[PDB]
Figure 1 (tube, rainbow over the protein chains, first blue to last red):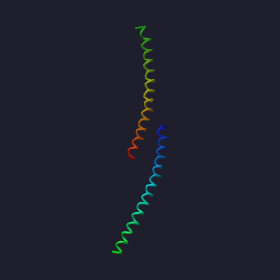
Figure 2: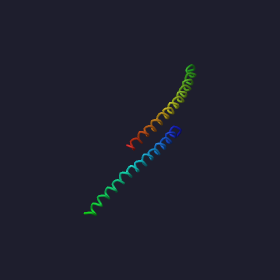
Figure 3: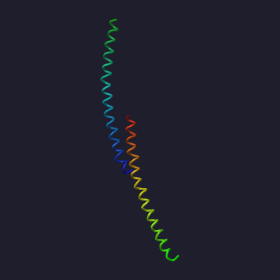
Figure 4: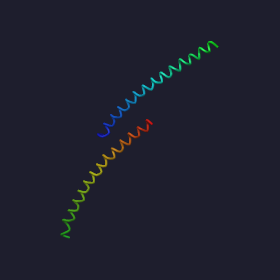
Length: 50
Length: 50
């Protein structure tokens, strides 16, 4: 009871932190995927010309 | 007979006392083991993340 309470809260904190890192992962991939959509679009143009 | 009776009772008393100390040992270890279960649990989380 008493010992594990501070630990439980510590875990809540760690989990939230984990959520922040995760948000950043989502954004990073946002950039990578933005890149893939645009470049793939250039190839699309190549096709229109062809 | 007569001499050893007071001694027998004294021994009963001592044995009971011994039982009290023993109860405390059980509790102490209760705390130590509680600690080991929780901390080992933290390591478990490390594994989940890994």
